[PDB]
Amino acid sequence: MKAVGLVVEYNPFHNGHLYHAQTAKLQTGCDTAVAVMSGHFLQRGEPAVVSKWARTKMALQSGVDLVIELPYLYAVQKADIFARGSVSILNELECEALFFGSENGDIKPFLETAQLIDEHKHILNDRIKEELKKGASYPAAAAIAFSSILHTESALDLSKPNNILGYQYVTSILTGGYPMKPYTTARINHIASATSIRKAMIGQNLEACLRFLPAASARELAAYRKSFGLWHTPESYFSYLKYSLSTVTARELQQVYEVEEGLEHRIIRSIRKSSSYQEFMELLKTKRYTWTRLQRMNTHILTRTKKQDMQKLLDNDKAPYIRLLGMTKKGQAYLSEKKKALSVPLVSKLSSFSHPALDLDVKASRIYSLPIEEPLRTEFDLQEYGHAPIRYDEDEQHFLN
Amino acid sequence: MKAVGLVVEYNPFHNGHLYHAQTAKLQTGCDTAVAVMSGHFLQRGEPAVVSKWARTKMALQSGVDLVIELPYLYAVQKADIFARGSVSILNELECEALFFGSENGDIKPFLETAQLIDEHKHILNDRIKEELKKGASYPAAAAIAFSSILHTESALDLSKPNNILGYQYVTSILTGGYPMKPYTTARINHIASATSIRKAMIGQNLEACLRFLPAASARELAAYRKSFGLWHTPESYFSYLKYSLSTVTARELQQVYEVEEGLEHRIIRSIRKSSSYQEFMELLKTKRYTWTRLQRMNTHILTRTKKQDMQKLLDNDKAPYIRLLGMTKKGQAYLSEKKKALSVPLVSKLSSFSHPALDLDVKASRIYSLPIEEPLRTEFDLQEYGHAPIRYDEDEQHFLN
Ligand SMILES: Nc1ncnc2c1ncn2[C@@H]1O[C@H](COP(=O)(O)OP(=O)(O)OP(=O)(O)O)[C@@H](O)[C@H]1O
Ligand SMILES: Nc1ncnc2c1ncn2[C@@H]1O[C@H](COP(=O)(O)OP(=O)(O)OP(=O)(O)O)[C@@H](O)[C@H]1O
């Protein structure tokens, strides 16, 4: 038996994510779907509207076999590091394939571009050279080099988000040396975006988005809103970011991952007079910082992650551990087969390992749950250490916990 | 001009404080009352019920001519350190008189006990070490070495808080040889304890205290809760203690003022499983910590005040500046008469002067607004800067700002 990897934030799990998990198998030919998922803070820098334990329960019912956490180390990063770490994880798990979405059903222009950029990298990087000399910025210089080779209309659209993610997936397998086959199909009960679906529940109104949500999801959601009493938004953390930037020194704020040299001063001026995450971000955005990148930096400023430590962990060539959130009986079976071949530990309960990348995952949790009104917060906190992998039986509805 | 020094924290200012301010000017023959008081976080360790700005106005309308902030540096401290710098600042302002209420209306056992203990201070450390070398503990060997004297019928229980602080103002004066004469009287439309009042306001009673609280003071409290929607309590900050203990390693928390070696692990461990600030404490209790010492510590954790910060600042034998919060007609002329005499910065606008001890007070003023809901909180943080030091017209009630 053979495995198809999916890189997913599942924010939340909806019918579209279903179209992914089912097409993957049919198109690749693998009877096993393994997803590596961003746990509590995602690639664009925002918190998951629900815990990674809940979203696991949803995915395990909707056709994913193994749910592995994408360590925070790799998860809050722009696409290439995100892809590098997530593709390493799928590599560790011997997935025969990688199934990623774009607005194209075709895996070809991802391929053709990759080599082109793979082979021209010298020409390219020598072409970035010449341009800085003319006094242009680096993004300028980079844009000028790309366009010489890449203005041939291939045409890979490096705008459409998930295509960028596709390119870096294909990229990472290529410089990785992984025996992995990238697949893909076109994105599209017509299906809704995860975004618009989020606004729904955020408006307290989860009823709008139901037909777009698989059944298992709605309950687990309703159960999560019933269990812990909120849905999680970025504005839930503003109060704690405001504490963070209060209790730090501009020398200390310089060392937080993604705070570039000099910005820490602008950072502190803005936060004092910022009455919302919205306003704060409004005072923050620069030419040097995209919207999303600020959400990333702000999340780091939330977990108080230092550059040096982050540099330490990125230097590792492979995922430090395999963090097991959940599994079906196929998942369990696929795992126990390959487990002996896993070269890094397999974490199910947190007492089975100690690594700096994992405290980071645990810390992210302890921060993530802050919005839950006490005592309800503390019950939640028992989960990271408490919650053992969630086990579903595809012979319907058996959770064994 | 003659001024009487008042060492106070008005939380709130009650009938015991109003009587204490009028008898201050009566019994000490001074035309002016100068108060040094804790701004936002106090000696007992807890947050002020209401901002230093408003509590100032319960004082100016109750007979205090001048109000200076006791910096966090001295304010949140053991009673030996607290008394020292309060007295230090009142002597800086050239107060010729000091006035404190007490469980012992008698200064004489205070001047006795003080003059008594130094006469023997060699006899003590010997009986201490003689107990110490015999395996006795610190407070035991001291309680034995101290009960080797003083233990006559005199009482003056220094098991009583007022006698403790009172002995400590007097000690700082004698040991300092200040030209400032100390005064005391016993503790007695009515009069209650600020604490039994406080717990009465937490018990959803305000006008209940109107028997036990003056007009201005009661006028001032309502308009606060009106604007910011709260009275500040220790629990209110619990979420920020969780959050702050959730980012910090053992080593770094180890470096926090008043965190004893190895107590970090217990703290980090205890905060996890505590769904209440009260629960957080019981777990933390070890005989080397009183409850106040544990409350004082939770403050230094919140504000992230470090041992090296503190000891470096505690070391000096003078006060770093005079922060002026507010004043009367009388108070102004006194500040104008003694202005040129101050050997340290008179800080009216915060803009004028920056000092690490000053950095500390503002950091505490930012931590103080945190339970306040925005947009109010963002505006509350305006007060530490663009607030003209308050001024009030003694004769027929006018604030000039
Ligand atoms: N309707 C859909 N059609 C095709 N692929 C989908 C669909 N919904 C999700 N996927 C795929 O599922 C995987 C995980 O999705 P993820 O949680 O990252 O959402 P997303 O596609 O980024 O959301 P959005 O569509 O709002 O941009 C990705 O490979 C994604 O392309
Ligand atoms: N009712 C009272 N009788 C006598 N002295 C008082 C009274 N209230 C306050 N004082 C004195 O006024 C001084 C300033 O007190 P502070 O503002 O520190 O409050 P406190 O003494 O902690 O409160 P409490 O009055 O509840 O003990 C203290 O030294 C205290 O002894």
Image: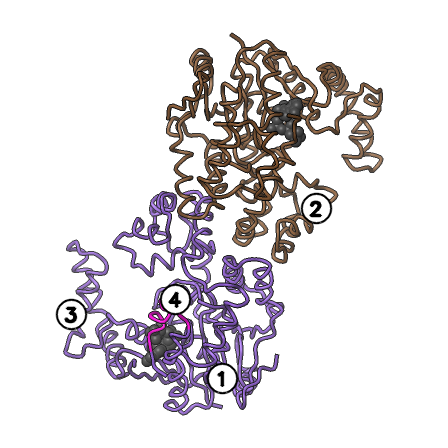
Chain colours: A brown, B purple
Chain-order first, disc 4 or disc 1: 4
Q: Which residue is mark 2?
A: A285
Estimate the spatial distance between the alpha carbons at disc 2 and disc 3, rounded to whole Å: 69 Å
Which residue is drawn at the image coordinates 49% and 36% (left, top)? Answer: A222
Q: Residue furthest top?
A: A1
Please report contact status of discs 4 and 1: CB closer than 8 Å, yes or no.
no
Residue A84, given in percent of the width and then of the height, sits at 61, 24
Query: In the image, A309: left or right of B158?
Result: right
Whether ligand 2 has any atom under 8 Å from the Cβ at mark 4 is answered as yes
Residues at marks 3 and 4 on the same chain: yes
Magenta region: which residues? B192-206
Q: Amino acid at mark 2?
A: Lys
Q: Name the mark on residue B65.
A: 1
Which residue is drawn at the image coordinates 15% and 69% (left, top)? Answer: B148
Residue A328, given in percent of the width and then of the height, sits at 45, 19
Estimate the spatial distance between the alpha carbons at disc 1 and disc 2, rounded to whole Å: 48 Å
Examine the rendering and report whether any part of residue B87 can be seen: yes
